[PDB]
Length: 497
Ligand SMILES: OC[C@H]1O[C@H](O[C@H]2[C@H](O)[C@@H](O)[C@@H](O)O[C@@H]2CO)[C@H](O)[C@@H](O)[C@@H]1O
Ligand SMILES: [Ca+2]
Ligand SMILES: [Ca+2]
Image (tube, rainbow, N blue to C red; front, side):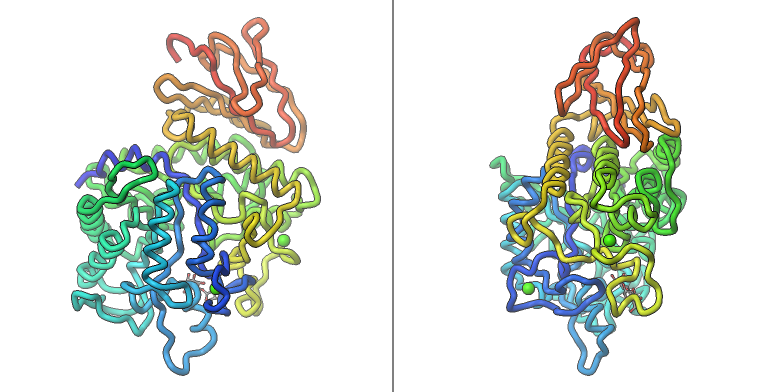
């Protein structure tokens, strides 16, 4: 059945902060895995997330996504690789209990309640295609069926329906990020989504505004592939929706290939490349709600990508301008967006940039986990420097701007310019029309823009600085610094646009 349309409006407003639990904040030094895949302290826990909720909210985020927190039970005599895998949460044993290296059921309850108190949605990480060999039966006596990886469908469906509704009914979480979602067939996703919607509509909590609300029931698939595969294995056909939201890996790659370079070194692209990527949204069915991230726990940090391509390093101003340009693109992107912890301060692993292959896992340096670095949370685990504070304040400005302007989060996109040096989108929702423009070049340039090309009948006003841009003979002349972004309100839109 259809993507439930109330969630659709809510989902376009999501600004999600992703935390990798084991590598985030060691809030209780008495517990923690103490080993894992990555260079972090490996003692991140639920208390550390609870300690970070004020920080996450002040960033302007309105939701948090935790990597799996369920109980990965060690088996006597298992090797250190298995010890490290237990720290990731992605090969779990008891889907219905909290891993004690992260915390207790009571602390997981406390976390969700306090997040809701502060106006944040909470999403958990559901791995419904695989698990550890010692999986334990559900409270209702169910087990997944088949191999440990991947499990068999539809034999395993009843079990994972029970998992997916349990955490909603017990903790009132607002939905699920779905790991490696193509391991679960589309018919199963339709039924799991029905279970999620039914469980969500069966409970309420009091949000920060004082209203009793159902948990969102949001579900976002991780399908690390191009649009044709995200459609085939995630969204389903037009008229027969499987899932309603999936991560926008294709545009993530276009963004890092424009403002940095990707892990394989493709980079130095321009606005034309970004536009071509956004245009491929036309391949998706009408119900698809792509979710743009710049990175995650499986991708190299943006700042390390900048160093890997010999593009920039934190000692150079351009390192920060490129972060701002990439984050500004996310802020202008309609639909849910996800920020990976540390991008807001330009994090990067000291001493690391080039790809490390031999012996990378025992070092914490493989591409697929090197971003799992100890979190730098201002006032909690770090005192930020001037450039770090400047980027974090910029991100707070973007998230605030996004919250106030429907054109950014749910506006219709019309590309105005997409060449090698600039990218200009017109965004409009109801009576909110603006221009998003971002430089894609290390050269200062002045952009000549016809008011008649953007349905502007008057001035343009910068929504962050308030600078007014007036037309002469119907044309604006806008100076763009290298990789500068501008959010320009169309103060008087034309009768027709
Ligand atoms: O030692 C093998 C392998 O383990 C890790 O890969 C994990 C990953 O960390 C988990 O998050 C999840 O995706 O499962 C993977 C195993 O299937 C290391 O990240 C990886 O480098 C290493 O080769
Ligand atoms: Ca700890
Ligand atoms: Ca580095």
